Amino acid sequence: VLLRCYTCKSLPRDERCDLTQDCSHGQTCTTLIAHGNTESGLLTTHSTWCTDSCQPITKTVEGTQVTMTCCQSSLCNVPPWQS
Amino acid sequence: QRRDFIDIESKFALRTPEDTAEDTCHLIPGVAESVATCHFNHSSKTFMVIHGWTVTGMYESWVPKLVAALYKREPDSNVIVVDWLSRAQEHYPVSAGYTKLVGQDVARFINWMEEEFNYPLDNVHLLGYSLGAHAAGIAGSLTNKKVNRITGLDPAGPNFEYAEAPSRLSPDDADFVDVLHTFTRGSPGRSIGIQKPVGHVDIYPNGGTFQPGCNIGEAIRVIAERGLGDVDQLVKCSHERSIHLFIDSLLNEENPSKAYRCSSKEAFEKGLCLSCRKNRCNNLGYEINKVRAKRSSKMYLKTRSQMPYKVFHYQVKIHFSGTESETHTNQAFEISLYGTVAESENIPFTLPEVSTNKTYSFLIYTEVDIGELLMLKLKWKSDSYFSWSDWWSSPGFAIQKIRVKAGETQKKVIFCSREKVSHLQKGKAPAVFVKCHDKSLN
Ligand SMILES: N#Cc1cc(-c2ccc3c(c2)Oc2ccccc2C=C3C(=O)NCCN2CCOCC2)ccc1O
Ligand SMILES: N#Cc1cc(-c2ccc3c(c2)Oc2ccccc2C=C3C(=O)NCCN2CCOCC2)ccc1O
Ligand SMILES: *[C@@H]1O[C@H](CO)[C@@H](O)[C@H](O)[C@H]1NC(C)=O
Ligand SMILES: *[C@@H]1O[C@H](CO)[C@@H](O)[C@H](O)[C@H]1NC(C)=O
Ligand SMILES: [Ca+2]
């Protein structure tokens, strides 16, 4: 079964992904979410793409919450605040 | 029988997994009973360790280390140490001459094993260091059938650089010839290690000129003045490193160092050669992929100063965007990599030129296994005492994305600024970028 995922780069919290790409066979949907303070105050971003190796993780790199999520449904990789 | 072999000056010890440092048992050419006395395993493969030049006439410290590692990796094999210490203890050009005779001694011994015991030559691996790499080459060029493999460990350069294929190690000498070039510093024909490729695969660790932890860096060198000389040459550190890199590969079967095919060391040091497509990469050492190409393929990599020598290579591409046209020369930066497993902060690197709306590629390597990359911090360094002040005017660039290609995992990763643009300003706070894309190159 071939998947279609949302493919967007570093989008701000209040903005939904328009771009969608057909994944290569074996590929899964992924979402990276960064959340931490910046010069323009606190900021939440989301990036989505077709990945090969998918590892769900949640680490706080240099005081920024990074969350990685995987899903096997088509167009499923939508950030929590948009599902 | 023995009568037809007494002219053979070279001795052949069958060293054991428990007796590594001594030539206890000898395999006497023409005396078939000596093979049983030594307990040669006719079922297993054979390694022939051929030493090089010596001013002392004693086996160096590396000989038991190499024997021990071959027996750790291959516990049932036969590890034969070739003794040519008398001939290897003459004035260099004279011992260089004796490589023909040692090559002949070895070939006759190999051919005898085959004739007398019908031992397969496809089960023979020749490891030659210094002049021994050429003694191995000559031996291989004189056997009845071709030997399986020849490893050249920093082959002797003086009087061999311009020697023709029959007088030195060359790819026709075995089924597969792999060569580590670790001390090629100097003019052609005047380097201690041979500069030209002489195998099917020719690996040049750290460009092959000298090894990390072996030289006296240019700064220390200038300060020391008339005092210090070429300690590396004298101590044979860089030269010998090829033996330690090989040993490392035998002790780390599961994690080999990867070498990358490249047009030049200068191109490699720009991070332009990091692919694995059409055998453009290979494993350094024992676990090499026996790819015999049409042309001699030169391969590069970086290593640590000490065992285990493996480092992770990354190519980093940055487009330096800006509003006003400015050009900066010999600029120093620091890059910090944050992954899933670990991190390596403040990795320095410099760029010869930094100019508005231009892209620059560079190599970044690290000992740390950081895992999958998540974050990237970039700092543009200043040495001015006023850089801290907001009153101090400093140049800057707007950087949106940073493209990274990891050599070991063959992955292209895009990192992009948290805000619309990250301002990289000389002497100020670091610009932050977070992963926004992955791509397995396969
Ligand atoms: N391992 C290793 C290794 C060593 C050399 C090496 C040893 C000696 C070299 C030399 C090279 O350079 C050459 C090169 C070409 C021609 C001559 C020459 C002279 C000497 C010379 O007189 N060295 C000073 C000490 N000598 C001792 C014997 O007594 C005379 C003085 C080369 C490749 C190797 O892999
Ligand atoms: N005439 C004359 C002359 C030559 C030598 C001489 C000494 C050392 C030599 C040598 C020549 O050969 C060369 C020649 C060229 C390049 C290297 C080299 C290496 C070493 C070497 O053994 N080095 C390794 C040292 N050890 C490192 C590990 O720890 C133990 C010490 C001595 C007296 C002389 O009158
Ligand atoms: C010879 O090598 C084989 C492994 O290939 C091993 O099983 C056998 O025990 C060895 N025999 C002797 C005589 O050492
Ligand atoms: C660099 O490119 C941007 C547009 O991408 C432009 O605004 C800027 O003027 C250019 N810089 C120079 C020095 O021309
Ligand atoms: Ca040859």
Image (tube, coloured by chain):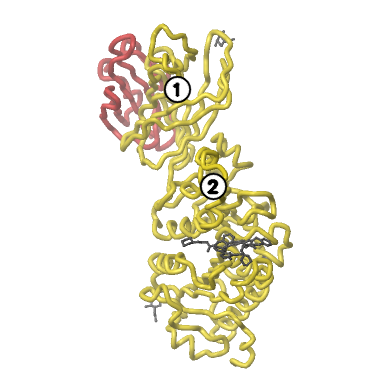
Chain colours: A red, B yellow
Q: Along the line of sight, which residue is nearer the eye, B144 or A40?
A: A40
Ligand 3 picture quarter: bottom left
Residue B180 x, y percent position in the rendering? 55, 55
Question: Which sits in the foreground, B259 or B231?
Answer: B231
Tell me residue B43's x, y (percent). Answer: 45, 78
Asked if residue B434 shows in the view, the reply is: yes
The kind of secondary structure element at disc 1 is loop
Q: Pointer 1: what residue?
A: B381
Quadrant of the rendered structure where residue B111 is? bottom right
Residue B123 sits above or below residue A15 on the image = below
Q: Are marks 1 and 2 on the same chain?
A: yes
Name which residue lies at 38% across and 76% down.
B19
**Going by the image, does B71 lie left or right of B216?**
left
- Dots 1, 2 in contact, CB < 8 A: no
Q: Amino acid at mark 2?
A: Gly
Q: Residue at x 49, y 75 (%)?
A: B80
Residue B281 visible? no
Of the two numbered discs 1 and 2 on the same chain, state the one appearing first in sequence: 2
Nearest to the observer: residue B344 or residue B408: B344
- The secondary element bearing badge 2 is classed as loop
Q: How packed is label 1: few (under 14 Cα within 10 Å), some, or many (20 or more)?
A: many
Alpha-carbon neighbours of circle 2 within 10 Å: few (<14), some, or many (≥20)? few
**Viewer-side residue, B250 vs B23:** B23
Identify the residue under disc 2: B227
Q: Looking at the figure, which quarter contains the N terminus of chain B? A: bottom right
Residue A9's x, y, as percent? 41, 20
